[PDB]
Length: 182
Ligand SMILES: NCc1ccn2ccnc2c1
Image 1: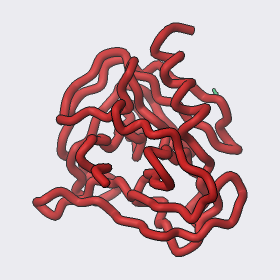
Image 2: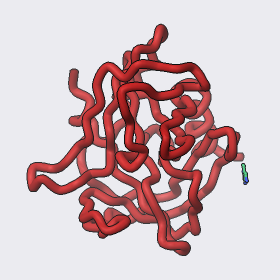
Image 3: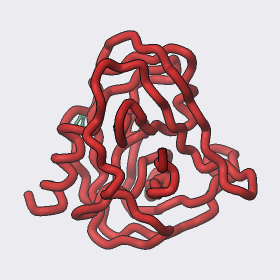
Image 4: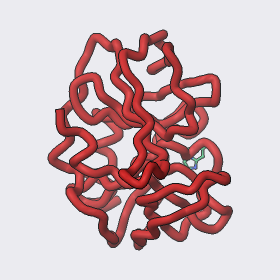
């Protein structure tokens, strides 16, 4: 509908896949080469389905901060025969608040879904499903099960992936440029 949705659509069309684990189907953001991200509660194993193709996992790392606190991001390297468009230049360097964000989702249950969520707060600490979690972004939109792994963008920035909600608010884990130095 406008330039925020234009940027969101460009990320979804080239830099997402449908990831299936034993815990469900998730939007999965490809960042560069064969490296993608997914919420840690997806419980990635040795094998994952990527667009319904059986795929070996070459590496999976559940990120924590230097306080040894959950960040709810898992970085996955996939045994896939094709590289992602490198979008690391769209990742913020520091923790921040944002105006006018879009949460975008693409699964078999939730195809071609775009949600204008408005203002995004640097929330920080969240007890997420009982797990102390840091670097949480918050938006005032009633997100639902199946939106996990959804991409949060503003024009020219990929800022987070959706990891939970409380019925009234939605919560995303930050993506930072420093997670993807190779
Ligand atoms: N219940 C499935 C679904 C899929 C895509 N959507 C886009 C907007 N609302 C929906 C709902």
